[PDB]
Structure formats: structure tokens, C-alpha cells
Image (cartoon, rainbow, N blue to C red):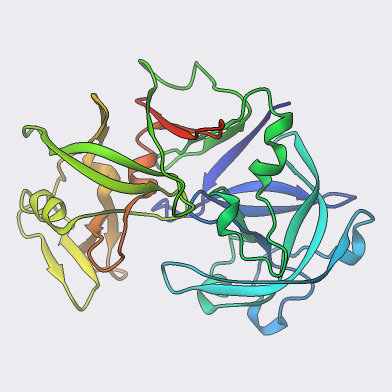
Length: 330
């Protein structure tokens, strides 16, 4: 089997991407944030505290003839941005782009934190990291990819995120028309539950490539590119007027600037992030200070190849017995 679904930016900055997902019988379609940095499929629901729902589409398990309460199961998650959610668990039929999994754990939110409530465009998350990170207790549950893997033509999914434009998530096949050149594969460590890999270095604009190992995670659920402070300082030093602002929470730059590109290494191959992809717009409405898309990871504990980096590439998440990641230009 295969599946193919379009993923669409939630706003003009590409702050996140939503993909339609069918849950239940008859189908209830929710727009979920596919997140290769977490492993819970959770949704706003008929059980979510009413004051914490503000425009999202909800899953109502009582209206699904295939929904079954997973007795005793609860979940609770906190994300790197400080947001969180928790609730109980159903199993139900879940389909993405024509690919169907029966008995998928659908984690129904009873509580969500304010940032979820405030984002009317995201109806929940669909985790695509490794199932060892799934938070369901007392019986940990499998991700949608893990449940579908054995049925897929090839045990892979691909992320093709657009810049200010829709893109595609495919399951079970590699669309050879979707990228240029060849796909370069690189090793993955699953020891932390992430799609964790080692970039071979970077370049700023037309500058020379610096060979240096950068361990980080391929995370479609993080907006920006978070890298070591040395790397980020080298980038922003090429932008007149750029500075790290403690009050804003990162590097800012004059909105009048033209940003240089940033290149990262995948083995001997190179992925080029155009400068425009690094512009996240005014820090507040009407400001001439703009927020940078490359930020320091020093306060995180891990480097994150988020959407800013991934949307410059066609990315293969290879779930073979030994997982690997593949990157191609496009």
C-alpha cells in the first residue's frame, strides 16, 4: 500500500504545516501537524475542556462506529516550546492520503495548553518519531507509520515541505519526480527516539564550506533551524545590523536586509537554504526588526533541523530495520 497527502502552511510565515487526516467511521477529517520529533497522535475532541477549544475541528469518538475506548490508558506530553496536552485514548481507523490503519491509538485531549488553544488551524498532532517516545500509559502505543509499515510497498515516508506553498507527505514510496539529482542517505541513531543524524558541516552564503560534525534531529514539528552558537554567530555576522536580543528571544535583523543562504552538509552532498527562507518577519506587527530563522540551540540540548532546513530538501525517513535518512535537492 501507499498514501499521499498534501501538507499546507498554516500561515504566511510557514510557522507549521497541516495535513488532512481521516479518523473514524464515518470519517471525521482533522488537520494535523505531522511531527517527526514526537510520537503521539493526539486530537482536539469532544472531551477537550470547552474553554480550551477556539475554532479547532474536534474528534467525537461517540459518533464513530469503529472507536473503542482503550481502557485505563492515559497520555500526557510536553513539547520543547513549553506547550502540553493530555487526555485519554481510543483506538479507531485512521487514514492519511488513502493509506488506512485500523486500531490506531487516537489520543483524545482533555486538556491543552494555551498555545494550542490559540492556534485555530491545528486540530492535533500526528507523531512520526520512533514509538519508544509515545507517552501512552500504562501500555505504550505505536505511531501511525509504525502500524502501517508492514503493509507499505517500501517501509518509508517522505517529507516535501513547500516554501510559502503546499507540499506533500508520501507513505510507502519515493516519488522520483519530486527531487533533482540523487538522494544522499546518512546514518540515524534511534537512541533518543528521534530521527537523529550528523551533518557534515555548513557554509554561509558564497563562503567556503566548513567541515564539522553537527549532530541533530530532523523535526518537521519545529519551525526553525537550531544550531550551535558558533555556527549561528557565523551566519548572522554576515547580516548588517543583526544581533541576538535577549528580550525578543533570539537573533533579529533589519527587515530591510537581504539574507545570505545557508548550506548544510549531508555526507558529501550539500543542501542550500535560500536566504528568503530564513526571514520570519517582523517581531511584532509593524516593526522593522525581523526574526531570524536560524537560532542557537545552546539552551535546548540538541540541534534541530526544523522546517527551515527540511523545506529546502526532499527528505526520506527510511524505516527499514536499520533506519536512515535521505536528503535530495529539489
